Each structure stands twice: as C-alpha cells, then as structure tokens.
Image (cartoon, coloured by chain):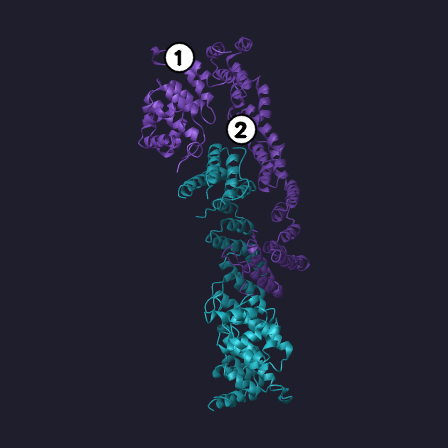
Chain colours: A purple, B cyan
Amino acid sequence: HHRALVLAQIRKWLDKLMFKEAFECMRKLRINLNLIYDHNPKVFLGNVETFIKQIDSVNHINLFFTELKEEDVTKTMYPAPPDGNKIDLVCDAMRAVMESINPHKYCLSILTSHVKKTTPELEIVLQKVHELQGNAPSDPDAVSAEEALKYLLHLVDVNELYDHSLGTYDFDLVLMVAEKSQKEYLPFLNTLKKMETNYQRFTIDKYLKRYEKAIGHLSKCGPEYFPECLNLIKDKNLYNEALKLYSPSSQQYQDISIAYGEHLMQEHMYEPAGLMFARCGAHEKALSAFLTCGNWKQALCVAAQLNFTKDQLVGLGRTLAGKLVEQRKHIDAAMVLEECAQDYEEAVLLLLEGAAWEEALRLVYKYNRLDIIETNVKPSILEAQKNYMAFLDSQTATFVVQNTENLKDEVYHILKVLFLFEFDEQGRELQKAFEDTLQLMERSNRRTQWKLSLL
Amino acid sequence: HHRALVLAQIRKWLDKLMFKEAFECMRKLRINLNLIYDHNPKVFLGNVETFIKQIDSVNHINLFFTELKEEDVTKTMYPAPPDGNKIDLVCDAMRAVMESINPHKYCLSILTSHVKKTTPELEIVLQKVHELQGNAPSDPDAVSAEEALKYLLHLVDVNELYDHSLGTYDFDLVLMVAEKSQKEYLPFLNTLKKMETNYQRFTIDKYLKRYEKAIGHLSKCGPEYFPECLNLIKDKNLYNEALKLYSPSSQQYQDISIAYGEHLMQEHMYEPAGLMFARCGAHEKALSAFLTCGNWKQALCVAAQLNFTKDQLVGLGRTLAGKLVEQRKHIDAAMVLEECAQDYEEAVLLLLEGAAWEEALRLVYKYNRLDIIETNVKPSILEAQKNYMAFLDSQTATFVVQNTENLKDEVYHILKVLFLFEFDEQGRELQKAFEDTLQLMERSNRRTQWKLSLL
C-alpha cells in the first residue's frame, strides 16, 4: 500500500497538467518516465507545449528521450483500472515545439529527437551538425559542431557516426569525428582528396552503400565513366532512378532503357519489358516481348510500327493465336485469327471451345458456312449441356465459399442457343436443374436474371 | 400436479413405441392427438408401419387425420423440457403404409390422406372414386363409389365435390353427387350431353377454369375451332403448353409462335420475342426485336438469313451502334461499327469513351491515323486520369460495402498506356494514390496484380 498512494498522486498531477510536480517526483523514486505519456496519450499530445515549458532544462528533457519506450507501461509495470507509432509521434510533436520556442537552446535536444526515432534519422542529424560548422559561433549562445559531437557520442556508435560524416562530404567535419574519438583512417581521406570533385563523391556514396546517390554523381564526372556507371545500375537494379538522370533522347538514356528491357525479360515480367522496349523505340524487342505474354493488341501496334506486309501479319496473327491458345485464352485467340489472317474456320472452333455460342454463330453466317452448324456447333452445345449438368452433381451433392453464382451468366447464354436449335428438352432440364441447385442454397448471390420464360 | 402425471406416462409410452396405450388414453381425456407425432417426429416417421398396425380401426385412424395440425403442440399446449411440411410428410408416409397393408380396408382412409394435404389433392381423390364405379363390387369386401361419397361429404364442400366430378367426365358419377346431396343443375348436363365427345370436355374444363387441359381438347375437335382456341391462348397466356400440342411445321403451330412473339413484344421482354420469331422463321420480326434490345450478334445472323447487301449491312451496323450507344454499351457499339460499316474513326472515339485504350489504339495503327493519338487519345487518357483521382477522394474520405477493388483491373489497364506515352508524373501519382486508398482499407479483396514496377 506504500506504493499505490504515490502512483495515485502522479496520475492526478498528470491529470491536472502538472508535469513538473509529477516528473520531479518520478525521477526521485526512479519511476519510469513513460508513465507521463502512457497515462494518457491523447492529452499529452495536445499539451506538448506546456510540457516542454515545465521542464525547461535540457538534461531533464533528454533524460526523458532516452527512457522512452515503444511499450505502454500502463499495461505492465503500473497497471490502470493514438494516431500511429508512439516513439515517432512523441519525437516529432516534441521537436516541433522545441523548434518554435528556441532552436538554439534546444539544439542538443532536437538532435536527440532525430536519433531516437524508430528508424534513427542520422542522415538528417548530420546535415544539422554540419550547419553548426558554418555560421558559428555567435557567442556561447549557440552550440559548436564539436560540443554536439561530444554529446552525440554517448548516443551513437562511433563507426556509424563516422560513416555519416563522409555522407556530408565536408572533410573538416570528418576529421573532427575521428580525432575527438577513434589514425589508420587517414589513408582513405588522403587518396579521396586527390579525386576530382564529382567522382570523389561517387566513391564515398558507393562506399556507404548509398547507390541511388552514387549514380547521381558518376553521371556528371564525364562520358568515359558511363560504362563503369552502367554496370552499377545493371546489378544494383537502379533502372528507375537512373532514367530520371539523363535527358530523354540521349544515347545514354537509350542504353539504360534497353538494359531495363533485358533485365525485365530475364525476370519473367514480360509485359513491362514489352512496354519499355516499345517506348524507347526498340520495336523488334517489344514485339517478341508482347508475343511471349499474350498481349496481341499491343503486339499488333508494334507490328504496324514496323510495316508488316499483309502476309507477314497473317503469319503473326497465327503465332499469337497459338500463344493465346496455350494460355487457355480461346476467345482472344479466335479474334486474332479472324482479324489478322481471316481464318474463319479456326476462329469458329475456338469460340466454341470457349463457349462463345453467339459469336461463334455470327461468324458462320458471315461466311455461308451453315454446314458447320451441324458438324460442330450443335454437337458442341449439347456436350456443354452435359458438362454443365454433371457439374451440378459434382458441385451440389459434393457441397465453404461456393461462387457457382458466376456461371449464372454462362447458363443464360447457352440457354438461348439451346432454344434456338429446338433442344427444348435439355433446355427445360438445365433451367429447372440450375434453378434448384441455386435456391437449394439457403442456410446459415444477386437478383440478376438468367431465366428463359420460354422454358 | 393432477395432469403432468398423465402426460409423463404418455411421453414414456410413445417412447416405447406403445402407440395404442397412448392413443387410447389420449382420446379418453381429450388430449390433442398431435402429441403422438409432435412428441418426436423423427421416430414416428420410421415407425409408421407399427403405428398404423396398432390402431387397425379406420374410425380411429381417420379421427387422427382430422385432428392433425401443422403446428407443434409441444411448444404450446403440452410443453416439453424433420424433412419439410408436417401435414404432408405424415399424410404421405401414413398413406404408403396403408397402401401396402390393404388398399381395400383402408380406402376411406387413403382418400382422407389426400383431402388433408396442405393443398388438398381433390383431383386425385376423384380419379379414385371413379375407379370404384368400375370393377365394383367384389362383395362387401370393398367400398362402392356411393359409400365413399357419403363419407367424403363430411369433409368436402358440396360445390367443390361436384365441380370435381365433372373433372372426371363420367356423368353417372356426376349425377351420383348431386342426388346423394344438393335439380336445377340438370340443364347443364342435358345440353352438355349433346356436344361431340371432344368439345364436350373442352366446355367442362373451360368451366372449371382448367385452361391448360381445356386447350388439350379444342385442339382435337377440328380445324374450324382453331380460331376460338387461338383466343383462349392469347389471353390466358397458354403459349408454352399450346406449342407442345400441335406438330411443328404445322401452319397452326406457326400462328401460335407468332402470337407468342407478339405477346412477348407487348410485354417488353424483347430478347425472348426475338428468339421466338427467329426460330419460327419470322426474320423481319426477329430483326426488329433484336434491334430493340442490344443483341447485335443475333441481329447480324438474322440479317444474313435475309441476304442484306454490303450496304444494307453498313446501314444496319449504324442503327445498332446507336441502340448500343444509348444503352451505354460503348465497346460493343464500336465493334459493330468497325465490323459492319468499317467506320474506323467513330469506333476509335467510342472505345475511348468506354476506356478501351489498348483496342482504341490497335485501330489507330491499323489505319495510319496516328494523328488521332494527339487529337483524341492522349487527351482522353489524361482526363480519365483526373476522373480517377477525383474519384479516390469522392470514395475514400467520403467512406458500407465498398467494392472499389473492381476498378483494380481498369487502373492496371490505364497505367500501361500512361507509361507508353511519357506521362510518368500522373502515372506515379495514380500508382501511389490507388495503392494507399486500397491498403488504407483495413479495419473490422484479392491478391491480383495491377502495379507497374515501372513506376
């Protein structure tokens, strides 16, 4: 009972926005500092200004930062009868208030609110410690690039604080960190200095594994470096970000576009590669990329961009109809056959293979081939008939989620051609049949019509 | 407590399949007879044979029938700590046992199990009382058509028992009912007798409102009666059942088919009418029926069955493309325009109107009209772009069931033509945009891909 009396107090203090009283006492009985947020997140955010202002101190408001955990201490350590990420909301919201009130007094704390994010923003923290090199000192009123290094050192690995210096490119800043911490690193700098401005920065970023940026340099230190650069891209997969670098219509932006074709190819994402080849004017490549997947619409555009003869098109049409057949895209294969090669007969058989009765039939009359009705169309209907019945045992008796309400359309369609051809018996059979096996599904769909009043 | 002791007994008797003990006692304290089924339906059905056999009596097993209600007396009157319709299961199951054991002893009861169904089968009951006229008497061992009328009279309205006599067509049976019950009905019979066999039965069925059967007669009493008959059909809507009457290829089956066309027309079910006209060889009618709805596939078949000129087809194609446009079926309207009238330009604009970018574009190259890309295609893409963004505020902020996962396809499709045309900015914009407004929907879909690695 000795303890619960204190925590009571603290919960009432934080309730009356008295953060100092609460905090001063928490720190003296070593109670965890998260309480003062976790006790009520919606209130603490929305009163950050009056929080910051009550612990003016920078030791105190940094001691809060180090102690701040992702987890709610109200669930576990101090049991009690948001927007998103906690560490981030608090580091952000707190920093915006410190930014406003006095960026110069709170420098060391604003840096700490970058280092402590769920993904420490050390890139940003060092662009800030760099600016402290220029425009300093303005009296002991501000903080020097060295007073901040002493402090950051307690919070950031030394190998990681050094690796990030180099990121800024400012060498005096880079020395500052090695000397005010961990002289067999002087070889790197002393050869680095002897590189031209642009290629020096490339080597630094390729070394820090920052490839997207390291390309942003090699693109500037000359055209005899384009091959060394093209390599990086090829196998760091920097295709997207390298295109925005060189001007379009450049013979350099051209090679990067082809290599992106070739990489997309070798990755079995064939359609994107066909679109890239086709944009950068590589028609012969885009045609065999569009062929390998079943994109005939595009395939025929690229083919016109190459001026195929009426025959070379007939030949192409066939090749595609094959690729589409082996992708079970029968209706599509038929429509490339009747468009490109005027193969009336093959098209009609493929339409029937994909249960396109009405279109299978339009073609028959468009060509005086009424003989096929007997040979192929009526037999193909009657056989589908059976495969549709046999499927309503197979899927009725033998039955989680049954979307057999999407052959709702397909039955509608075959019912009409059944009636047109005097097959009433099997018509009424399927009508009745599909009806029951469709309502006989109510336990614990849509209103779209497929019936034929004619049966 | 005086009562619950008895009901206890009865529940234990019915439990030990002792129906007689139970029943004998139920009838003496006027307990409701439903108890002996409602106490356990799954058991009583499955022991009907031993039930029937224990009340051999026919008074007793008829007294059960009259007392049998649809409702469970176990829920209400006698509270207790199936397949379908109760009255029907019991009347059926009980009748099948009485049929087997001795159709002649149980005649009066088998008739009662027809009269008591949820929809009393009086048609069937009278075909049975008719058969008792022929093959009688075979001693007092059976029941005469008159001994059954005395009994049925207690159970069936007299006007309804008479109306059904006439249904059997046997006049001696018909007299039997009027005399052994309610002589100013003799005019009907005495003129009815003077009709030929077939037309006499027509008049009886038209009088009993049994039209489907009354047509089955008029179709036989001559060809000068076809007009009187055709009328009945027209306005009793007996089109389906009248077709199975006359032989196909009959000029009588022809007129019934047209009138069914005309009736389907006047009912705004235009597609069925177009199929009927088209089956019975009424092409000119089926063409304007297929036109009025948007069925161009069929429309073009019927048109070939009439040998339209190359021009009369161009003209038809246009007419359909209009009907399809006013049914917002843009892609279809375009495909009738490029097929029937070779209107390249109109088709391309309509495809764009229905967001068929890839097919809109195939056409452009199939005709050297690259100028349209500028004038019409690129502008139409960019505008869709906006209507797709503006729709992701309109449908994201302003939001039960949101199937905005079916424009999943349509975005995929427009993304590719965006990239082909150097519109990366609006590409990445829509990619990013649609992505969030698609995941930002998780609270309390599919895995189909629409992304472009190229953005």
Q: Quadrant of residue A415?
A: bottom right
Identify whether A152 is placed above or below B295. above
| Chain ID at mark 2 | A
Nearer to us in this view, A296 or A440 = A440
Quadrant for residue B283, please give it. Answer: bottom right
Q: Mark 2 and mark 1, same subunit? A: yes
Residue at (32%, 24%) from the top-left corner?
A: A54
* Three-letter amino acid code of the residue under disc 1: Ser
Cβ atoms at labels 2 and 1 below 8 Å apart? no
Residue B452 shows up from this direction: yes
Which of discs 2 and 1 lies nearer the camera? The answer is 1
**Where's residue A179, x and y in %?**
49, 9
Q: Residues within 10 Å of mark 2 (few under 14, many from 20)?
A: some
Q: In 3D space, how far apart are the residues under numbered discs 2 and 1 (Cα atoms)?
A: 40 Å
- What residue did someone put label 1 on? A144
Instruction: Identify residue for label 2.
Output: A240
Report the number of numbered marks: 2
* Among the two numbered marks 2 and 1 on one chain, the one whose residue lies closer to the N terminus: 1
Q: Residues within 10 Å of mark 1 (few under 14, many from 20)?
A: many
Q: Is residue B370 left or right of residue A27?
A: right
Secondary-structure class at tag 1: loop
Q: In the image, residue A287 lies at what x, y percent?
A: 61, 36
In this view, B317 is above or below B179: above
Three-letter amino acid code at the position of disc 2: Asn
